[PDB]
Length: 49
Image 1: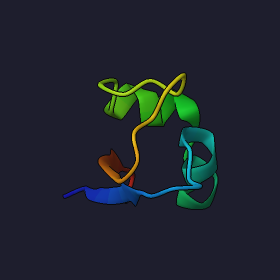
Image 2 (image 1 turned 180 degrees about the vertical axis):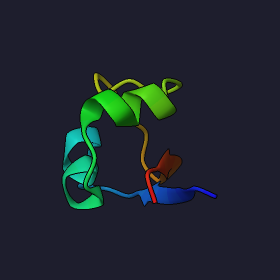
Image 3 (image 1 turned 90 degrees about the horizontal axis):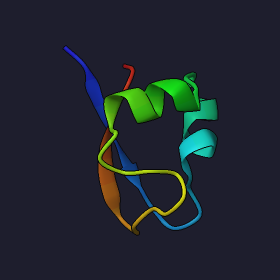
């Protein structure tokens, strides 16, 4: 019963985490497949609903 989030140009891990109400520790703990050192445009990831 979770939720997802679409990563578009201008959005980042920490950034998206802010509004989402989460932190990098979580974003990276959920979607470790993508590191903050380099993100791809238009990438759908999981977030705390």
